Image: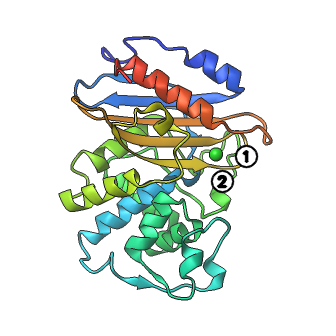
């Protein structure tokens, strides 16, 4: 509260030019200062759930030492659109760790569905998020049905604030044991799908990991990230968008611009 939005930023003009709604929550983990805009509204997760899915797998691996190296074979029926990694291993299978990396770093859809099944489906991932104290997150459906992004539909949504709070717990806090925490960070750092989103606002000499989401309808897309500016504490942030019409286009540039405004609001020189 007292450290929230100490410096106002023109998020309203940005979302008006975009023609929709932008939700932002950014936390300076050193001072506790935050930037918050529509931060408690629900927005569709789209593929951004796959980051939390990989964290849930890592959490289970703390109790099952063989889990990450377990080989998983799958049939052609498991390959759903946009499975760039898993399609190359159809004839061989992949390990749980490889599927998790593909889901995070390439947004591989077949990999995500296989891992979701392992965790007990959308309710199982939701249960994991409850277990770390996130009462907002909900996953309800599987890929690709979870991408419908229907206005007013709370299914398969969270808030920017809850996303940021949960990301902080998993990447910097105590929700994962130290080896699993660093593996989660390493997978996020290796993401290949986010170069035009939060990363476009982050100087090249800072470390960053992120997970994107893009629903394909209702101007709905998002990104969340941990950023390590040199010489100061890391920043955790989430940027989510949506728009009122089914055929509205998403914008990567708006996500990058919102991230820049969040870093400016926090007084982080970039
Ligand atoms: Cl895109």
In percent of width and height, residue 213 lies at 57, 49
Question: Which residue is at 78% across, 42% downward?
Answer: 246
SS under mark 2: helix
How far apart are the two marked residues, 1 and 2, measured between alpha carbons? 8 Å
Task: Tell me if residue 152 comes above or below residue 120 in the rendering.
Answer: above
**Nearest the eye: 208 or 162:** 208
- Quarter holding the C terminus? top left
Q: In x, y percent, where is residue 253?
A: 61, 32
- Image-quadrant location for residue 206: top left
Question: Mark 1 or 2 closer to N-term?
Answer: 2
Label 1 with label 2: CB-CB less than 8 Å: yes
Q: How many residues crowd around disc 2 within 10 Å: few (fewer than 14), some, or many (20 or more)?
A: many
- Tag 1's secondary structure? loop
Query: At x 55% / y 14%, what residue is drawn?
Result: 10
| In the image, residue 101 above or below residue 67 | above
- Check disc 1 and report the residue beneath it: 217
Q: Which residue matches tag 2?
A: 147
Where ligand 1 lies, by quadrant? top right
Identify which residue is drawn at 67% across, 60% down: 145
């Amino acid at each position: 509260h007292m450290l929230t939005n100490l410096v106002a930023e023109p998020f309203a003009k940005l979302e008006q030019d975009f023609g929709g709604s932008i939700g932002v929550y950014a936390m300076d983990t050193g001072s506790g200062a935050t930037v918050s805009y529509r931060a408690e509204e629900r927005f569709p997760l789209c593929s951004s759930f796959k980051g939390f899915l990989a964290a849930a797998v890592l959490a289970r691996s703390q109790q099952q030492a063989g889990l990450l190296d377990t080989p998983i074979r799958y049939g052609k029926n498991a390959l759903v659109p946009w499975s760039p990694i898993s399609e190359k291993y159809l004839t061989t299978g992949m390990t749980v760790a490889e599927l998790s990396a593909a889901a995070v770093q390439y947004s591989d859809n077949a990999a995500a569905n296989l891992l979701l099944k392992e965790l007990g489906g959308p309710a199982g991932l939701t249960a994991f998020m409850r277990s770390i104290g996130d009462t907002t997150f909900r996953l309800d459906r599987w890929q690709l049905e979870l991408n419908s992004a229907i206005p007013g539909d709370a299914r398969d949504t969270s808030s920017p604030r809850a996303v940021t709070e949960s990301l902080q717990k998993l990447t910097l806090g105590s929700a994962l044991a130290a080896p699993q925490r660093q593996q989660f960070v390493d997978w996020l750092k290796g993401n290949t799908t986010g170069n035009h989103r939060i990363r476009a606002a982050v100087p090249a000499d800072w470390a960053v990991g992120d997970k994107t989401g893009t629903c394909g309808v209702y101007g709905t897309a998002n990104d969340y990230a941990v950023v390590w500016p040199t010489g100061r504490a890391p920043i955790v942030l989430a940027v989510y968008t949506r728009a009122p019409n089914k055929d509205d286009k998403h914008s990567e540039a708006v996500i990058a611009a919102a991230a820049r405004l969040a870093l400016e609001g926090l007084g982080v020189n970039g």
